[PDB]
Length: 122
Length: 122
Length: 4
Length: 4
Ligand SMILES: O=C1Cc2cc(Nc3cc(Cl)ncc3Cl)ccc2N1
Ligand SMILES: O=C1Cc2cc(Nc3cc(Cl)ncc3Cl)ccc2N1
Ligand SMILES: [Cl-]
Ligand SMILES: [Cl-]
Image (tube, rainbow over the protein chains, first blue to last red):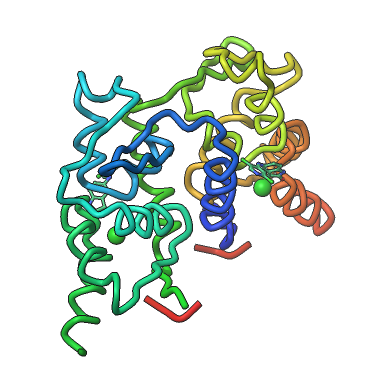
């Protein structure tokens, strides 16, 4: 018999993104080639099958630095990290291939699905 | 020119609640009288003006245990912690006064607003 | 607020 | 997915 506040989840995500922009309580650095991205492990786990696997591992859960596969494009990662914290995906003709490949590696099934649909249309 | 995934914020919150139920990456214990509640500092900050103030404080940001004011009812806190992680508020005739008082202390303005509306109706 |  |  609960009541529900419709905007609550969106408002929580907006505040987590504000914490990220101000580098508050970030507990991991994701290294993609020369580029570094600060984030919250819990947000990464909630969005990605790959980060979920990494941070539930008894040894990796304690690492402050995670290095991604050298094939991963920093721009594709940046677009996906922004999507994790906002629900908004900056999908463009010039980045769609790098975004789909990064989403497949990160195991973000809904992003992979929209990339496959957008590629099929063109 | 971004696209948006409607269910993303709700799905993120659902996964953060799953991490909470399994005690994964919880980094703080909230003590309310004899009762203890494990949570994620970032989720508490995103939902509460009080926890936002506590965990942005250069000294308190590093505490693993936070003791609430002895006037705070553990049941009222539990209902509010569940709301933070689910958007669902278990508001009942028998708990509304304890929920409103706890939401005022935690600075959760939308919960305070619905409690005032529900009390006014009765 | 809604009835979910 | 939608146009926000
Ligand atoms: O496409 C995706 C997105 C995703 C997220 C998570 N993260 C969780 C899943 C569960 Cl059941 N509990 C907790 C968490 Cl944080 C796992 C796999 C995938 N695949
Ligand atoms: O009723 C409320 C809910 C709430 C949440 C937060 N938390 C934040 C606010 C900002 Cl601007 N950036 C980041 C965070 Cl985590 C502060 C005050 C209140 N009052
Ligand atoms: Cl996804
Ligand atoms: Cl609220």
